Amino acid sequence: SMSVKKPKRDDSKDLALCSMILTEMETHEDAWPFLLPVNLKLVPGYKKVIKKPMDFSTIREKLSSGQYPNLETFALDVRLVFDNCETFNEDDSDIGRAGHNMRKYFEKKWTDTFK
Image 1 (cartoon, rainbow, N blue to C red):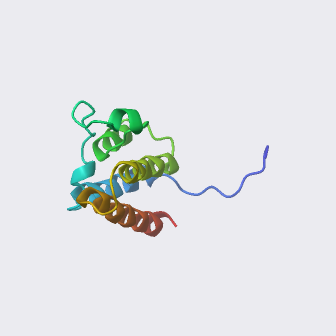
Image 2: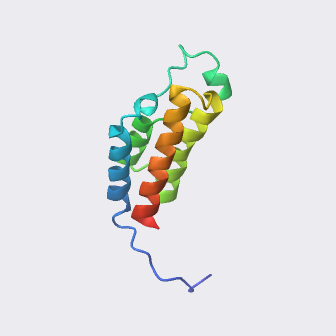
């Protein structure tokens, strides 16, 4: 509350460390469904159904331009990519499996770097 604060966690490396995680996600062999925004002209149903599209190149641009206020808003966009994927793709599909794999890969790196 006013003039009452928990001890200050060092967040000075968070930007660099999110960048590193994101590089690892970009270079994973199962990243291909997620590298670029889904083409809303060429994929029927996507625009209407997925209210907030997100992809790794959009997260990279937001990160590089100071549009994440803190490490939690970064994680929320990464998770949005996978939540969107599950919304639109059957689990038993190459893309559906890719999303599950990448979400696991992310959540481990996230826990190991920050928890």
